[PDB]
Image (cartoon, rainbow, N blue to C red):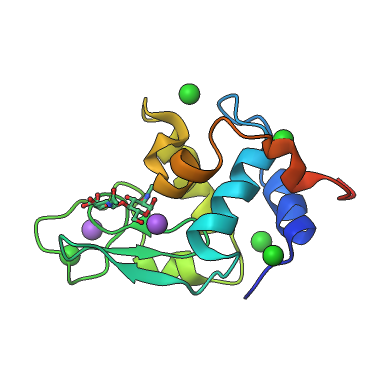
Length: 129
Ligand SMILES: CC(=O)N[C@@H]1[C@@H](O)[C@H](O[C@@H]2O[C@H](CO)[C@@H](O)[C@H](O)[C@H]2NC(C)=O)[C@@H](CO)O[C@@H]1O
Ligand SMILES: [Cl-]
Ligand SMILES: [Cl-]
Ligand SMILES: [Cl-]
Ligand SMILES: [Cl-]
Ligand SMILES: [Cl-]
Ligand code: NA
Ligand code: NA
């Protein structure tokens, strides 16, 4: 599924990401935008052979199991394919673990490089939330 911006904002809000670990909702929407262009089916292969999955491009090196990232962890205890669902629950729940892990949203490269320190509230501007 390719979410609309506000649709995703609302879904993320419903799933408790607004101000989760202090990260306002726009951070999460910004991250999703630049990680996946709001596409739940996005996958990208990393240089180490892991793959990033889903709307928040959660990687299989640490967070999910895709059966082809040897030596990796599965800290969200999910098949990576679950992160490709049109239902963002699994991604959100995993993202909550990630962002809780001490590094905040810096785990999301695109967030660090494209959202952090920007006016992320712009990403939820105009949305009914
Ligand atoms: C939370 C999450 O999974 N974020 C992704 C990053 O992990 C990806 O970065 C890449 O992650 C792999 C596995 O840890 C690293 O080996 C790789 O070096 C790292 N790539 C970079 C450029 O840092 C990122 C890839 O675009 O996608 C999400 O942000
Ligand atoms: Cl868009
Ligand atoms: Cl915000
Ligand atoms: Cl694996
Ligand atoms: Cl959802
Ligand atoms: Cl933080
Ligand atoms: Na990425
Ligand atoms: Na894994």
